[PDB]
Image 1 (cartoon, chains in turn blue, cyan):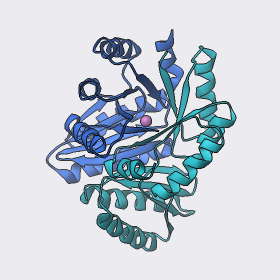
Image 2: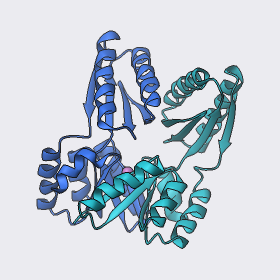
Image 3: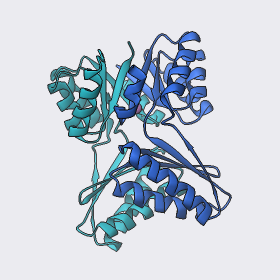
Length: 166
Length: 169
Ligand SMILES: [Tb+3]
C-alpha cells in the first residue's frame, strides 16, 4: 500500500512524513498544489510526488475571525449549491477553503464571489491551486530535473488539464 | 508516463473523466474517492489503482428543509473551527455529509454532542456513522482487493488516520 500525506504547509508536511517514517511506513507519497511543498517532500525522501492540479483553495485573511467566518459562510452556501466538496481549516488569521468536484465555469464564479465577499466584509482573499497547463508542464519538469522518479497528477476535472497530455 | 488520478464524487463524472484520459492514450489511470461505490465501479470498468480518502469522524444530517441543513452546516463549521478541526462538507440531496479530522478522540466526542444538539434545534436527524473508522476502511479495502484492486493508496490530511491505517495495514 501507499500512504498519501495531503500537505497544506511545508513544516506540517515534514512533521507528518517523519511521524510515519518513525512507525516504519515504506511508501510515503506527498500530495500538494504547492510546488515548494513538493520540492521539500522530494529532498526529505518522499517516495511519490502527487501534483494536485484540480479544485481551488480560497484563503480569507484578517484579524476579525468573525468577519472571516461570515465571508466563509457565503462561500460555503454557494459551493454546496454547485455540488462542491468543501474543506475548511482556521490556521491563525487564515481561514483556508479547499473546493473540489466542480467544473471550471463554477471555479471562476466562486473565485469572483470570494473577491466580492473580501471587499464587502473588508478582508483579504488569495486564490491558489488549479494553475495553468504551461505552469504545470514547467514545474513538473523542475521536479523531474531535481530527481523526482515518481510523479502522479490528480484532478477532479481533466477537460482543461488534458491539454498537458498533448 | 505518469499515473493520472481522477478524483470523483459522482460515478458518471468519474467514468467520463477516465474516458477523456483513455481517449488521449493515458496508460495508468487511478481513481480517488471517499465513495466505495465509485471505487468499485472504477474496477468494474477495468481500473486497478485506487485512492481511498474518506477517513475521520463521519456525520450525516437529513431533512426535507434544505435551508435548515445549510444552517446546521454553518453551525457545525463554527464549532469545528473553534476546536481547531478540519471539516469537509458535501450536500447530497436531503443529506448533508460531514467529515471531521485533525483532532484527538476527546475532541471528537465533544463535536458529536454539538451535532446531536444542532439536529434537535433545526428539526433534522443526525447519523453518527462509523464510515470514517479505519476498521470500516480496512473491511472496504479488502473488498476492493477481491474486486481486482492491484494498487491501493490511503490518503488523509490527518497523520492520526494514516498512522492507524499503517499499524493495521
Ligand atoms: Tb488526492
